[PDB]
Amino acid sequence: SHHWGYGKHNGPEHWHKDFPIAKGERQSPVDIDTHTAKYDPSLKPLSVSYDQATSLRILNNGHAFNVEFDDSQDKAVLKGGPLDGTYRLIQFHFHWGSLDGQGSEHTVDKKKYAAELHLVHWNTKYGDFGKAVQQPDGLAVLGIFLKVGSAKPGLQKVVDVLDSIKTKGKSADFTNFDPRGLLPESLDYWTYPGSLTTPPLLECVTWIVLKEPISVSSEQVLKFRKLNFNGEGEPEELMVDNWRPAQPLKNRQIKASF
Ligand SMILES: NS(=O)(=O)N1CCCCC1
Ligand SMILES: NS(=O)(=O)N1CCCCC1
Ligand SMILES: [Hg+2]
Ligand SMILES: [Zn+2]
């Protein structure tokens, strides 16, 4: 069978035929118009508590790679900001381009970054991820832009395992990785209600998008671009341009923490 992806024949313009929510009222990503976003003094301080994070594995899922965490206890959590309660880190992944001038999902005044990091968390009041994605406040995704410049030292362990997970369905052990090494200095952010940016495109996400990008080197992003969408032994389809473009804002407001 065919499957959704990022090519001409199965990319974002096709997703609505199997995932009609693709044309919904709270789809992600969106363009962040900085002049229209409003400071919200009701936002509480944002709390990223990752000191006890336990990474387990890295997986090439045929769309991106996921760095997976042990979420059987509150070992790595996001709280505060726009969030009510506690959200547990389950995985992170990236979206990136074929060229440095595109790759992000969110845009900032229509600016595209080279890539975007998504740290995915689920609301512990719903007990598991699968139940959380049946809820309008089930997930919180912390989004971080990547620009090309100086290397991000904390990213290099991710870059160096990618050769071992080149093709779809390959995984590798990935213990003792500290995701705090992927953050910028500032936690200043924009927030809005949205969706998963991949099928099934479920409208369950509180998005928290940091204003400050991280810098990664050209060499680091070049290694992202050597991954494959295809499986082993299949003709090579480089894993590039695995981003969804901006969707209509509709009846939403983006709030700023700053
Ligand atoms: N609607 S979809 O899931 O993106 N896909 C399009 C290509 C054929 C298989 C279904
Ligand atoms: N790209 S995303 O919206 O962060 N992600 C959340 C977890 C499920 C797959 C989609
Ligand atoms: Hg939902
Ligand atoms: Zn994502």
Image (cartoon, rainbow, N blue to C red):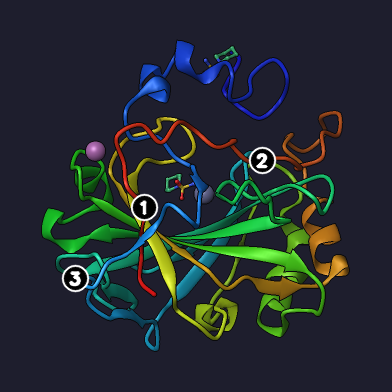
The tag earlier along the polypeptide, 2 or 3, is: 3
Report the side of 65 relative to 131 (left or right): right
Q: Nearer the viewer, residue 235 or 78?
A: 78
Q: Is residue 238 above or below residue 154?
A: above
Task: Count neighbours of disc 2 (C-alpha within 10 A) and say few if under 14, some if 14 to 19, many if 20 or more.
Answer: many
Circle 1 — which element?
A: loop
Q: Residue furthest left?
A: 125
Would you identify the image quadrant in which residue 212 lies? bottom right
Tell me the kind of residue under disc 3: Ser
- Residue picked out by circle 2: 242
Which residue is rendered at x = 64% and y = 50% of the image? 104
Q: CA distance from mark 2 to mark 1?
A: 24 Å
Above or below, 124 relative to 31: below
Dots 2 and 1: beta carbons under 8 Å?
no
Q: Is residue 248 visible?
A: yes
Q: Which residue is identified by label 1?
A: 254
Q: Residue at x 82, y 73 (%)?
A: 149
Find numbered disc 3 in the image and state the secondary structure of the residue it sits on: loop
One can see residue 207 in this view = no
Q: Where residue 42 is drawn, which disc sits there?
A: 3
Secondary structure beneath label 2:
loop
Mark 1 or mark 2, which is nearer the start of the sequence?
A: 2
Real-space CA distance between mark 2 and mark 3, rounded to the nearest whole angstrom: 35 Å
Q: Nearer the viewer, mark 2 or mark 3?
A: 3
Q: Which residue shows up at 81% across the image and 79% down it? A: 150
